[PDB]
Image (tube, coloured by chain):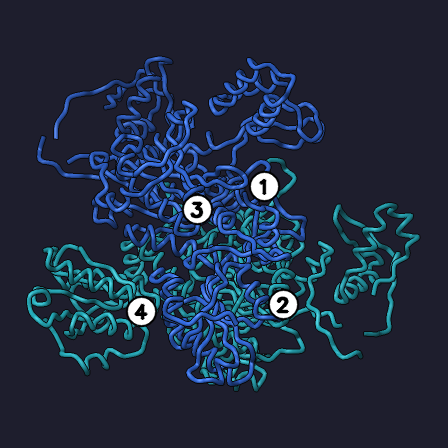
Chain colours: A cyan, B blue
């Protein structure tokens, strides 16, 4: 349970975030973040940096969002990064065919006048929804007679709609491009520079914290389905012969909710497991994937996501290996962090397309295309050299993948530098062995969707007080609260301000983010306002603080609203240790006088 | 002087930044930043936050880059954000007409067989280059017979080329949009939310730190002319009746190089002035603009930009009021920080286009369109209401601006909600006075181009050592150096590592960013490597550090390469105070034994 309406009202009112271009009617899937929201987001990102980039000594890079077409063609985004879309024929309103058909089905299955066998049929359709191609989906649309859910009219046949934002780089029409749909490709393109930076050694990891774009058909669902979004993505390159993480024992004792592919197939439920046990039993393939899963868990819980509403779902054979961190919200289980485990065929693709060897290189202890120069020479004269040097760099996965088509269809076609070439029995294969080893690195890909993580934290930390007027507050951990300490002085009189100034300065010296409250009203109402945005602690300075000696102020805990009274010069250290988790509120109450004034 | 080639080699080699998509041949005006470059950039941004956002309690927001067309139409970017472009007729290579004509002229002026009077004529042409319209520029191209500078062929007549990146939001063709060319508009659209957040009071300031885009015709000049760039932009809203900054005396004593518009016109040189004097004499209009100029200076010098290569150039009548922070580089004087001072007509424009009143409101102490309902009613029937309510919200600047056209051409045309309306003598004017005051805020607009600032710091801090091999280093201030302290241990032996670990942990407790050097070679060569990226301090731990008691390590200053020897437990505090400017290197040498071993 979560009062989404009330929470959303608080989020819009205190301006954590709001619909972008609101005064222009707004734009779907686009959101502006306000001061408090920006503070929270910056805290999220900083905590993320110190977690991952700092603990793992990750190589951070910042690539461009603007990406020329060939780069995203080579990566398969031009051909495969799309959603099936259907159009109303009367007005033309676009719909994502997936969720539309799914809606129609989930509706019909839940109808009294419907047979058991058909309900079965439809369960069968849903549990295979992602395998369906264009024609299959068209047939499915016809056979279930799917109409528009607003107008009830007929729908155009499903057609592939690419989700990348299209544009043009330069003033001609010769460099068409896209806004990047992910930040991984920029890391892959810089793989050589990064490997060099790491003195040629494996393993290593690169990270990027920046925006990505996705021309979502019809965004609803708030922050969950957006068109422009900030991602925190790690690419961990490891030797496939070295799938063992030296630091796995640090997270091996963690107890996580795991939702295996087998459990999903067999209608089973997720189960709590020790991470080490899960790896030991082959639920999680290796300890690199396991390690990163564990630290993803630790990060998510650190920023305020509830453990009882957090699970890790493995991807089924139709969605290589991939575990997603999923949180339970009012929109149901949503993916917030992806974590792929796979051979980096990306490096191979870009290597072929650019003729630049993107490969690791390990020395050992001293343990193929066979073209016809003549036929290619006659076919493509001066361009034969290019076909040749293309072929001389292709890796075994590709020599295989094209050997198949060389057999079956008796062809297989490439494209290099300029354009394309149809190779047909101008080729052959070579064998034997010899010999430094070429290492095509496996990659673990943790992909953090900061917006969804933030919204999850919103839903998991939102609470209401007891009163007739339902005062709301956010149980933000101090590490991500917009700021940690509110300083509430009673007056502006120039004998108060020295205390306020000293308190602020000391708070800054102690690394406690704070803010002096110059707001209007009763103490409890001001504290209600600061609670409303999830500020963790409060220090109120009254007349007794100023005029009586020793000078003591009141420390108030956000969650409990309970207070103590302490020497104002000691409060920065207390708030520091509180926020850093060095001491509990109970530890503070046990050493300082209680205070309900 | 600056060895740009050598410096660029160091920048590319250590991967501060490099051409984006290099393996794909690269893309002009697009750059990826590597680990060291990302560290420097993050330090730049953090220092900027603490300077401006922290010192001024600025309201930070994060708006979207994706912007629908109407927003940028209302702001005048669709019609006016463009460069004049000429095309080669043979190949079609595009050129920015400005710099091309300027190049041709600057060439011809510098020719022996050229008359004095024509040189004068051309000086006259250049000193008016920005006033020329399309036809004028075409005539200028014909009359100076400008050809392609590569092929020598004829050039197409100059044509307006808009610099915004075009795209489409959603799956239709009904929401055409752009990548934002600036971040100010997102602040203007949220003006109401931000004013509310500030409890309705003026003055206040909003900030944004994020990317903007500019489809530059033909980028050369490295980081200086880019298509995608990170900006740090502040919008300071102030009551025009309150053009006085309460904190101006903090910067009033600063001595700045000021390049007035008058000095530029009269062929005069820039001159050093006390800021307060400059304001007093009307060189700088007010103390808000003056204050922000002073703190811009302070920020730029703080991050390593040389004062002797930093000036503030006022904008001439053809470029309201605007001072730009300019730095002297190998590309000459480049603009790195803009600082506009003007009435916010933007708010008025968006107010009219959206019918949403974006205005401040101050209570005092108790001191127009006159349409013809009938004529408009007959002209536009049901749409008369919309014309009406549009007219009821227009501000005096616009009632004036359209009164003029109402006279001259006897027309004037608007556009609201749906589309356009031609008003022709369906209107009139109303007068008198009465009466809370509507405040249309003046704005000071500091716009920081982080890329250019960073490159400037590169050129101003790059130096070479004396040796035959020219070892290079960067005199980065500790506050922006990639990291402050390199820890150089001699061995990996498990009696060294406790010292290294304790030193690292203590360094972290003291807020000193550091890195343990596990590199390959002599001490001096490792320190050469760390100097090469501008690391400010070094702590070398040798065998005498480990095995002899008390345990002392060596502290090495980057610039001087001079060293001292101190108790390894005291070094974190010393490095902290050094980096924070609390003590000098001389202060350290005066208290600890020298060390040239």
Asked whether, in this view, residue A293 is left or right of residue B232, the answer is: right
Q: Residue at x 12, y 60 (%)?
A: A496
Disc nearest the viewer among 1 and 4: 4
Closer to the N terminus: mark 1 or mark 4? 1
- Asked whether residue A145 is in view, the answer is no
Label 4 to label 3: alpha-carbon separation: 40 Å
- Residues at circles 1 and 3 in contact by the CB criterion of under 8 Å: no
Residue carrying label 2: A199
**Residues at marks 1 and 2 on the same chain:** yes
Label 2 to label 3: alpha-carbon separation: 34 Å
User: B52 or B460, which lies in front?
Assistant: B460
Residue carrying label 3: B306
Q: Is residue A21 above or below residue B350?
A: below
Closer to the N terminus: mark 1 or mark 2? 1
Chain assignment, label 1: A
Residue A241, located in which quarter of the rendered image? Answer: bottom right
> Counting other residues with Cα less than 10 Å from the Cα at mark 3, is it few (<14), some (14-19), or many (20 or more)?
some
Disc nearest the viewer among 1 and 3: 3
Q: Residue at x 64, y 71 (%)?
A: A201
The quarter of the picture where the N terminus of chain A appears is: bottom left
Disc nearest the viewer among 2 and 4: 2
Where's residue B419, x and y in %? 41, 30
Label 1 to label 4: alpha-carbon separation: 44 Å
Residue carrying label 1: A168
- Residues at circles 2 and 3 in contact by the CB criterion of under 8 Å: no
């Amino acid at each position: 349970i979560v009062d989404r309406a009330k929470m959303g009202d608080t989020l819009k009112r205190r301006f954590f975030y709001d619909q972008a271009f609101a005064i222009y009617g707004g734009v779907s899937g686009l959101y502006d973040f306000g001061p408090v929201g920006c503070a929270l987001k910056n805290n999220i990102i900083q905590t993320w940096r110190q977690h991952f980039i700092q603990e793992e000594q990750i190589l951070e890079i910042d690539c461009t969002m603007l990406t020329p077409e060939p780069v995203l063609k080579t990566s398969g985004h031009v051909d495969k990064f799309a959603d099936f879309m259907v159009k109303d024929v009367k007005n033309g309103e676009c719909f994502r065919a997936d969720h539309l058909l799914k809606a129609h089905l989930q509706k019909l299955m839940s109808d009294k006048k419907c047979s058991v066998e058909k309900k079965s049929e439809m369960e069968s359709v849903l549990a295979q929804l992602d395998n369906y191609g264009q024609q299959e989906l068209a047939d499915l649309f016809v056979n279930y007679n799917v109409k528009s859910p607003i107008t009830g009219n007929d729908l155009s046949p499903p057609v592939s709609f690419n989700l990348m934002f299209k544009t043009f780089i330069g003033p001609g029409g010769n460099m068409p491009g896209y806004l990047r749909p992910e930040t991984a490709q920029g890391i892959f393109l810089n793989f050589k520079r990064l490997l060099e930076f790491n003195q040629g050694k494996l393993p290593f990891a690169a990270a990027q914290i920046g925006n990505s774009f996705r021309n979502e058909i019809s965004p609803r669902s708030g922050l969950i389905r957006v068109r422009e979004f900030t991602m925190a993505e790690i690419e961990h390159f490891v030797d496939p012969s070295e799938k063992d993480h030296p630091k796995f024992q640090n997270v091996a004792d963690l107890h996580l909710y795991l939702y295996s592919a087998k459990a999903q197939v067999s209608g089973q439920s997720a189960r709590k497991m020790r991470l080490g046990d899960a790896v030991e039993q082959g639920v999680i393939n290796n300890t690199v994937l396991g390690y990163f899963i564990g630290r993803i868990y630790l990060y998510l819980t650190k920023v305020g996501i509830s453990p009882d509403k957090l699970r890790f779902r493995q991807h089924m054979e139709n969605e290589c290996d991939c575990w997603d961190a999923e949180s339970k919200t009012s929109y149901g289980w949503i993916e917030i962090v992806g974590c792929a485990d796979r051979s980096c065929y990306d490096l191979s693709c870009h290597a072929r397309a650019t003729k630049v060897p993107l490969v690791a290189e390990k020395p050992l202890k001293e343990p193929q295309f066979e073209p016809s120069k003549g036929a290619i020479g006659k076919a493509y004269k001066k361009d034969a050299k290019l076909v040749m040097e293309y072929l001389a760099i292709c890796d075994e996965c590709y020599i295989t993948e094209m050997e198949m088509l060389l057999n079956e269809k008796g062809e297989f076609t490439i494209e290099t530098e300029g354009k394309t070439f149809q190779l047909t029995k101008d080729m052959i294969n070579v064998k034997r062995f010899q010999k430094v080893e070429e290492v095509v690195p496996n990659v673990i890909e943790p992909s953090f969707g900061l917006g969804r993580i933030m919204y999850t934290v919103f839903e998991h930390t939102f609470h209401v007080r007891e009163g007739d007027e339902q005062r709301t507050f956010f149980s933000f951990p101090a590490v991500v609260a917009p700021f940690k300490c509110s300083v509430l002085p009673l007056s502006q009189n120039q004998e108060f301000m020295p205390f306020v100034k000293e308190l602020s300065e000391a708070l800054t010296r102690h690394g406690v983010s704070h803010k002096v409250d110059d707001s209007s009203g009763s103490i409890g109402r001001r504290y209600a306002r600061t609670d409303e945005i999830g500020v963790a602690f409060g220090v109120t300075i009254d007349f007794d603080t100023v005029n009586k000696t020793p000078h003591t102020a009141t420390l108030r805990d956000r969650d409990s609203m309970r207070q103590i009274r302490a020497e104002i010069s000691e409060l920065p250290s207390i708030v520091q240790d509180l926020a850093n988790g060095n001491i509990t509120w109970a530890d503070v109450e046990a050493r300082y006088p209680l205070f309900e004034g």
